[PDB]
Image: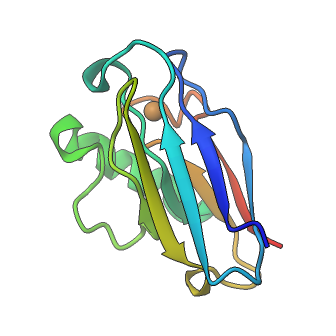
């Protein structure tokens, strides 16, 4: 069972993956986010956020309004299954979540909630396999 993934968000507003697989034998799954490049948090800060496909737009919109000092997420947002903090270059963060939080049939999306980043396609799918 492969129960973690290392993902990078760079100074050019991209993740180095578009698709995450979660082994369904995993009890927990861990995302390790890092930020190659030179740009600080306030310029090109990234996070990793998990929601259902349907909820992503809302999470992003409300997170935009919540703003930078809230790490671009509505605090305690019920739609956020898991999330890292916002990180700048040189910084890192991990998040671990229960795999039981994912449903059969459902469609899940990961993304950066930082202003404009998801629109520029800092997103992809997350799928139970
Ligand atoms: Cu970002």
Q: Quadrant of residue 71?
A: top left
Q: In which quadrant of the rendered image does the N terminus lie?
A: bottom right
Quadrant (top left/top right/bottom left/bottom right) for the C terminus: bottom right
Judge from the rendering whether residue 24 lies leftward or rightward of residue 122; answer left or right: right
Where is 46 relative to 32, above or below? above
Return the x and y of residue 34 as percentages of the image width and height.
Answer: 49, 36
Q: In the image as oriented, which residue stretches furthest toward the left?
A: 69
Ligand 1 shows up in the quarter that is top left
Side of 8 where 35 appears, left or right:
left
Say which quarter of the image contains residue 79: bottom left
Q: Is residue 90 above or below residue 12?
A: below
Residue beneath the point at 31% across and 40% down? 64
Q: Is 32 positioned to the left or the right of 85 in the image?
A: right
Whether residue 92 is situated above or below residue 54 in the rendered picture: above
State the residue at coordinates (41%, 12%).
38
Image x and y of residue 70, in percent: 19, 46
Q: How many marks?
A: 0
Residue 4 lies, in percent from the top left, at 65, 61
Furthest toward the right, the residue is: 129
Q: State the residue in front, 25 or 80.
A: 25
Chosen colour scheme: rainbow
Query: Measuring 74% from the left and 85% from the top, which residue is drawn there?
Result: 104
Q: Residue at x 39, y 53 (%)?
A: 84
Residue 49, horizontal then vertical, whole percent = 47, 54
Q: Is residue 50 left or right of residue 62?
A: right
Which of 92 and 104 lies nearest the eye of the viewer?
92
Is 123 in front, or is 24?
A: 24
């Amino acid at each position: 069972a492969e129960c973690s993934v290392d993902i990078q968000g760079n100074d050019q507003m991209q993740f180095n993956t578009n698709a995450i697989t979660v082994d369904k034998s995993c009890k927990q799954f861990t995302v390790n986010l890092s930020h190659p490049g030179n740009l600080p948090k306030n310029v090109m800060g990234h996070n990793w956020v998990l929601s259902t496909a349907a909820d992503m737009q809302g999470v992003v919109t409300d997170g935009m309004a919540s703003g930078l000092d809230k790490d671009y997420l509505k605090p305690d947002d019920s739609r956020v299954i898991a999330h890292t903090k916002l990180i700048g270059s040189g910084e890192k963060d991990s998040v671990t979540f229960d795999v039981s939080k994912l449903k059969e049939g459902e469609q899940y999306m990961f993304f950066c909630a930082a202003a404009a980043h998801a629109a520029a396609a800092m997103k992809g799918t997350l799928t139970l396999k």
